[PDB]
Length: 185
Ligand SMILES: [Ca+2]
Ligand SMILES: [Ca+2]
Image (cartoon, rainbow, N blue to C red):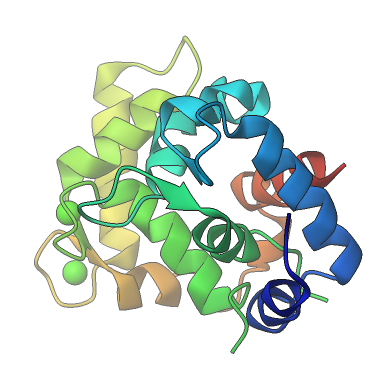
């Protein structure tokens, strides 16, 4: 059972209401198959909405900090705070875009390489996008973001290229809004 001081601190750290947090704890609780107060990666497969998504494994893996194979409710709620609709909080443009950047930056060297970009594109596009056109999408996308000529995208570049775009209305970002709502509801 979630203690009230725990609930008040989450509320302040994350921006979820008392009510939202209570609902998410119950979802946390139903997902905890080992009844040990934490979730493993495999536990996240019982969120089929997440798991079936093309970036599912990546989104899930992102709940786990380096070295750790179990996430607690606090860790869980902190990650979800990145997914909240805007309305520096954890759902700020920067924090939210950093979560997204992290989906692409598989080796965590803080740059998206051409290959890393290709791997996400291959996961997301439809049946009729050719390997050739994949190369051109990856190259143009790098071209548009790259301002220091390393042919890789840094976080600043990733953010810059979206500086005057409404991130909040992007489909992938709206997935995250939807996910957080469905976990709660
Ligand atoms: Ca990288
Ligand atoms: Ca660059």
